[PDB]
Length: 101
Length: 101
Image (cartoon, rainbow over all chains, first blue to last red; front, side, top):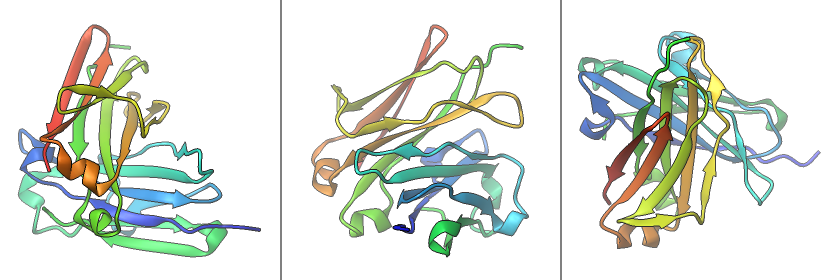
């Protein structure tokens, strides 16, 4: 079967993604086929405040999704945050370190 | 269940994606109830609809909803405006977040 593995980009936390001492960060999982992709953070060590949204299908016929976590801003630059993306149909896994801006 | 207004976080294109000659803005909409939202994007002050995709809101473990909206641009489109904004309308409130290249 025809497959296409995802490209993974960081959604970096910054002063602009932070409100009242809570920072949001994420990963963008672009242009894969077919479904599904699953995402974890720090190999499943980070589960609190994780939200992964459903995929969108583009006219190209390829899917994209994003996953996010909210963390204390005091953790930024100290705690490593890695998004783990698994695309079984293409036998691909991607880990992307998400670092502050 | 009590109504909850969304938290909105807008992420600009990553340096990595721009270097890969693409640009995607990601608008993360979280912790809202009920599940109905409308998303509109602006380039500077002008409404934009081209290149917009939005997820169907999905229930999280906290029983509230989350969604993503994406605006696909060229790196040249991104750099040529002063700002981009995502506006999220929910239950009589609109919340707009703005980012700059």
